[PDB]
Length: 241
Length: 234
Image 1: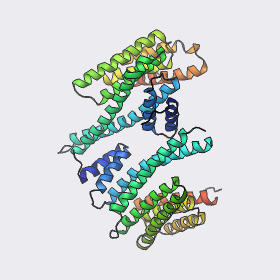
Image 2 (image 1 turned 45 degrees about the vertical axis):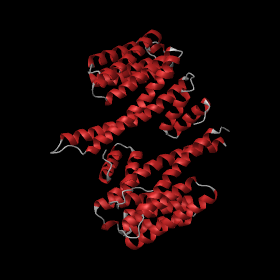
Image 3 (image 1 turned 135 degrees about the vertical axis):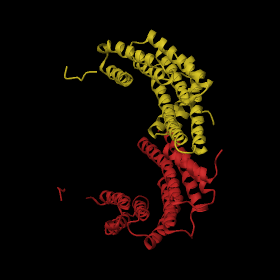
Image 4 (image 1 turned 90 degrees about the vertical axis):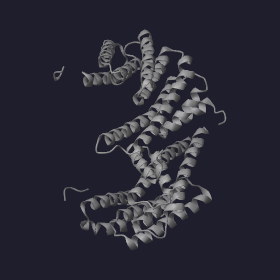
C-alpha cells in the first residue's frame, strides 16, 4: 500500500513475533528488506524466524499429506481419492511460493548488499536452506538443478566461513550442520555428511577453551546437534571422568 | 480439480490432520454453502476449523492489547492491534453469516439446533471481547439471546450429561462472568449444571463418561477460580 517507514516495519515484525503471527512477521520483514538497507544481526534473525515458521508449517503439512497419499495408493484394492494429491499439490505450490520469495529477497537485496562475512555466510546458508526445502518436494530434472543450486550456495558459504570465521563461530557451526543434513538427506552422500560433521565438531572442540562463557553456550548447543546427527548416522558406556 | 461437497469434506479432514486450520475452514465454508445439512461429524469439522482460526486471532489480539495497555507512545501497536481486530471481526461475521444463512433452522434434531445456536452465542461472544461503545451492547444482547434460545431447547430435549448441553452451559456461564458482568448468574449456572450432570454420571457408557466429565472439570475449574476454594487420601 502506501510507503511505510522501515522502523515501523521492524517494530511491527517484533509485535507479530510476540503475537505468533508469522505470516504477518514475514510480510513486515520482506517490506523492511525491500527498503534497501542492510539488516542488523537482530533483524536477520527476525527475517529468518518469520520465514522458518511459515515454511516449517508448510513442510510439516506436506509430509502428513504425502504419507497419507502414499499409504492409500499402496494399500488395498484401489488408489487414494484424487483429493489427497490435489490438496498435497496446493500445499506444495504454496511452500514453493514462500521459498521463491525468500530466494528472491536473498538474490535481489541481501547477498549482494551484505557488508561482513558473518552476514554473507548467514544469507548464503539461508539460500542453501530454501533450495534444500524446494529439493524436498521436487521430483524430475528440476530436482537435480535445485540440488545443485543448494550445494553451490552451501559450498560458497563454507568457503567464506573457513576463511573468515573461527571454527567455534555459531553461524559457521550452524551452516556445517545444515550442509551435512543436505549431504545425507538430499544428495544421498552419507559419507560426506559424516566427514563434514566429524571435522566441524573436532575443529570447534579444540578451541572451546578460548571462549567466553556466553560464546561457549552458543557453540556447544550446535556442536550437540552435530554429535546427535553423527550418533544417528554412524560406543562404550561412560562413568564419571 | 475436485471441489464438490464430498471432496470439500474430505479435504477438510486432510487439512485437520495437516493442522492447516484456515484451509480446513475454507473447505467447510464451501461445504456449508452447498446448502445441505451437516452431519454430526461435519458440524465438528466446521467448529474445530473456525475455533482454531479465531483462537489464534484472539490470542494475538490479547498480546497486542496487553502491550498497548502497558505502552499507555508508538502508533504501531494500536494500528497492528486494529488490523488483527478487523481480521478477527471478519472471521466472526463469516461464521455468523454461515449460521444465519444456512445452518440455523427451526426443523432439525435438538442436538444440531442447540449446537448452532451455541456457536452463534460463541461468535457474538468473541465479537463482544473486542467491541466498544454502542456496538458492544447490541453484540452482548445478540449473544445472550442465542445462548438463551439454545438453553431452552437443551433443558427440554437433552439429558443433563449431554456433552453439547454441558458445553453450552459452560460457555453461557463464561459469557455471564466475562462479558455481561454477572458473576452471580455465571456461578449459579455452573453450579446447577455440574450438580445435575453429577447425579446421572453412573448411567453413562465409558466413552460418554469421558466426554461428560471432561466438560464438568472445566465447570468445576471455573467455579474454583470464581468462588475461591487440603485433602489427604479419601
